[PDB]
Amino acid sequence: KSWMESEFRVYSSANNCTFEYVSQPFLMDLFKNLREFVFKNID
Amino acid sequence: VYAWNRKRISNCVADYSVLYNSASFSTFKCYGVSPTKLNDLCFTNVYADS
Ligand SMILES: *[C@@H]1O[C@H](CO)[C@@H](O)[C@H](O)[C@H]1NC(C)=O
């Protein structure tokens, strides 16, 4: 009685990785909510 | 050796003092840097070739 992710097809290959970081594992829940994000690429 | 494994290490606190005193090393030679200075040095990336 709960959705479970089973498909991830985004990149065919991954070679010469230049960074990797994984946060701590958790559970995502599968009236609204607003998620705002600011992405800045500097220096 | 022909397929030597390489691990990329970044974005972490390297513990040189504990690492160098963990096991028994029959050979330990550093070039361009002292083993005890690494605790005070910062680097962009590390490559561990085993
Ligand atoms: C990954 O880097 C090596 C040398 O650093 C290079 O020979 C190789 O072509 C690179 N991989 C790709 C897919 O370009």
Image (cartoon, coloured by chain):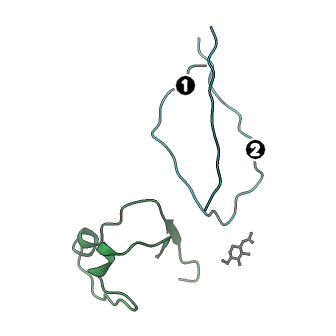
Subunit that carries the residue with mark 1: A
Give above or below for B31 relative to B11: below
Q: Quadrant of residue B12?
A: bottom left
Q: Residue at x 67, y 31 (%)?
A: A6
Q: Residue at x 36, y 75 (%)?
A: B41
**Which numbered disc flags the more N-terminal residue, 1 or 2?**
2
Q: CA distance from mark 1 to mark 2?
A: 20 Å
Chain letter, green in picture: B
Q: Quadrant of residue A38?
A: top right
Q: How many marks?
A: 2
> Viewer-proximal residue, A38 or B5?
A38
Subunit that carries the residue with mark 2: A
Picture disc at residue B20: none
Give above or below for B16 relative to A37: below
Judging by the rendered image, the residue that carries numbered circle 2 is A10
The picture places residue A30, in percent across and down from the top left corner, at: 61, 19
Mark 1 crowd level (few <14, some 14–19, many ≥20, 10 Å Cα):
few
> Viewer-proximal residue, A18 or B37?
B37
The picture places residue B26, in percent across and down from the top left corner, at: 27, 87
> Viewer-proximal residue, B12 or B2?
B12
Tell me the quarter of the image containing the C terminus of chain A: bottom right
Give above or below for B20 relative to A23: below
Chain letter, cyan in picture: A
Side (left or right) of B48 relative to B13: right
The picture places residue B27, in percent across and down from the top left corner, at: 31, 89
- Which quadrant of the render holds ligand 1? bottom right
- Kind of residue at disc 1: Met
Tell me the quarter of the image containing the N terminus of chain A: top right
Judging by the rendered image, the residue that carries numbered circle 1 is A28
- Kind of residue at disc 2: Val
Side (left or right) of B20 relative to A23: left
